[PDB]
Length: 4
Length: 172
Image 1 (spheres, each protein chain N blue to C red):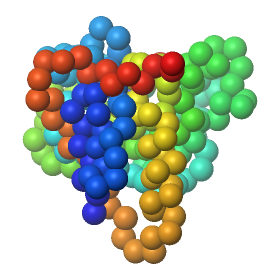
Image 2 (cartoon, helix red, strand yellow; image 1 turned 45 degrees about the vertical axis):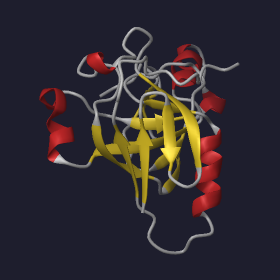
Image 3 (cartoon, rainbow over the protein chains, first blue to last red; image 1 turned 90 degrees about the vertical axis):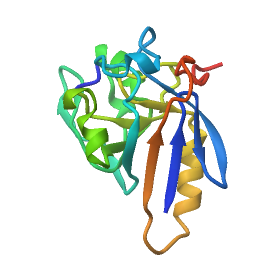
Image 4 (cartoon, rainbow over the protein chains, first blue to last red; image 1 turned 180 degrees about the horizontal axis):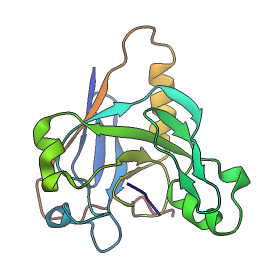
């Protein structure tokens, strides 16, 4: 899970 | 043990104080959107990893990707260049990893959501995490640095109304  | 509560707008540390807090991207700050990617965090129970581990790991400098870590870490804002000045402003300066702490929470939303943190950006939104008033991290340090024993923190997320999950954390 990325958060960009 | 400390059981924090988060109702969409307020993060409560029982017996200590109430902190402004926000979850979800701007159009997704709603309890009924909590299974949409980057929306308000799903309701349930989460463990906080408050052990202070210093600078967060950088997984890919070119793409501004921070690696996951299970503790309290800092965001390397001082070296941000170009696009990472934008992207890391959405982290803030501090983040605390959250992990689902029971099966019901973990199975929420088909299990498709994750990577949750508490962090202290001042944007008024959060990419599927919980943005908290920065003073929370200063209270956390003060309340824990003099304690010698076990330090166990959880947060229960429970939205009791349809109100927007925005506690006014955008910088004034």
